[PDB]
Amino acid sequence: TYQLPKVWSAADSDQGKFSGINQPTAGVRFEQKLPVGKEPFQLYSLGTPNGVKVTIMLEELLAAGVTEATYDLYKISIMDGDQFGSDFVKINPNSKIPALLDQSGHKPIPVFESANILLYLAEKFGKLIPSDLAGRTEVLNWLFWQTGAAPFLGGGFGHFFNYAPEKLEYPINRFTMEAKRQLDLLDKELAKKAYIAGEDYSIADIAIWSWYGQLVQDKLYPGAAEFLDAASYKHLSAWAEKIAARPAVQRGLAAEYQEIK
Amino acid sequence: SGVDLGTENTYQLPKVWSAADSDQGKFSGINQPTAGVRFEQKLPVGKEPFQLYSLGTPNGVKVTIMLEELLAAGVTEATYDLYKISIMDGDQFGSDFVKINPNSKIPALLDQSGHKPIPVFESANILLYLAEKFGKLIPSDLAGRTEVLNWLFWQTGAAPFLGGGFGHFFNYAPEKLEYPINRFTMEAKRQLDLLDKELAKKAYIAGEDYSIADIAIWSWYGQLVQDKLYPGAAEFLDAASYKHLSAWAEKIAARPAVQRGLAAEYQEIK
Ligand SMILES: N[C@@H](CCC(=O)N[C@@H](CSSC[C@H](NC(=O)CC[C@H](N)C(=O)O)C(=O)NCC(=O)O)C(=O)NCC(=O)O)C(=O)O
Ligand SMILES: N[C@@H](CCC(=O)N[C@@H](CSSC[C@H](NC(=O)CC[C@H](N)C(=O)O)C(=O)NCC(=O)O)C(=O)NCC(=O)O)C(=O)O
Image 1 (cartoon, each protein chain N blue to C red):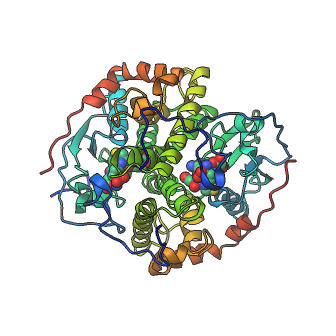
Image 2: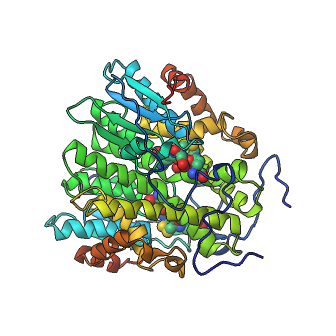
Image 3: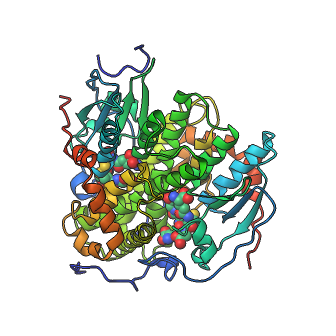
């Protein structure tokens, strides 16, 4: 039996793979100057579900003839703690990738949260979200949905299934049930629509594919697709395959992250 | 006649997971590994431009606060009908509610001010929708807007750790489990520290002006540090040690539209 204290103080507690990285405090841990290249967009990121959203988006824009959507891509190693460097924290004080700088204009604009970066780029160039209120709203319903759902998938299911030191039954069941509910939701939606927000591929599809599409394609945690009965979600699976064959998606996944040190 | 979207105005990990009747505490009857409608339900639709199907939770109060801030700012067209969706009763799985929000979470909003109604779900998206509709509580310049959105999306991506992680394991799980509690308490504290440090530098989360991002953040973190959420949690988290966050939380709690949003009455649907 573990005793719950009145006031929590276990700063040194085991956090699995991210022991040392995870802390009860935020902010800068060391001085860091990040490189800045010539392209309008500087992307400080890593090839994770959240990072690939942004390279995919940029490649989709490039593939549609938006010539300004070129970017410099730099590797932020989250296991090394690069996300706690002074320059990175300036861009994203939450110390998570992806983080972006738009230096197309007079002064650079810092953008973080992967879904927000997708929205920012979509509105800047008028691509991959409808310009009519009804269509825009439905994309946003699902884009925000993804932002609020993925934490359970990655931070709940993924953590306990793959990165916690012991396999803990109760958390795994709790978070697996939620992951399945989410998969079932998306499957049932995609049984009625070509893409998540209707007839047209959108930033919501990019956001959702990067987590749920890769998941059911068995590209994420080892054994997870099988554990979750991924193949049983036929409409989600068919949509994930369709999106995986887009050239911009393939280029987004294959993008080269340059060293910062 | 209800909502009409068409009409005019040591444990062994198995190889494949199998569900169970596993006791999740309070929400065991309700939670399932599938989504969708569970029964037929016609929701009331009133006369006001905004129909809000919700409950007085951290996610729900964001929207009543927003609507009341808009009204307090002179937006006479931001009146609403407010209806109680009981999440313990499973009202969120009724046919009309699922038609507005297939994810079956409150809050969900119908904007029937235009020619056809527009369903809006996700509390943060509802805030953004209302802010853009009326041009208030988000800046119109790109830099100002982007900073608000950074924090609005942040809130949406962070609250699951606070409610679904910390809240659940601290308050709702039948047993107090050490590893989950330490994981999610540490993350909650990181979030509180992050916010405290921002609010030491700025009057509101995105700068000198109050925004939808403050509403979204306050509704969780503000209420949390004011000891209004799970019993013992503010003490457990050392909430009073976050002095800039706590002062900001008090400041916003004193706003008249915030009080009115908290006090709103949720009408019965059945
Ligand atoms: N909502 C943000 C999430 C960004 C994010 O999670 N970034 C991760 C890498 S993506 S890789 C997937 C990621 N895992 C992690 O971040 C692992 C570390 C974490 N501290 C932990 O203990 O779980 C995850 O589950 N995310 C949940 C979600 O998407 O909402 C990161 O930089 N981590 C650095 C750190 O934590 O120090 C967004 O969409 O931009
Ligand atoms: N991202 C959505 C979340 C909305 C939401 O979570 N709504 C809750 C009530 S807010 S009350 C706070 C809420 N808790 C719950 O939803 C409790 C029920 C849940 N199934 C469980 O067992 O954990 C929570 O932790 N939220 C996490 C977050 O905000 O990201 C709901 O309708 N639940 C019905 C259901 O689950 O069937 C939003 O911002 O609108």
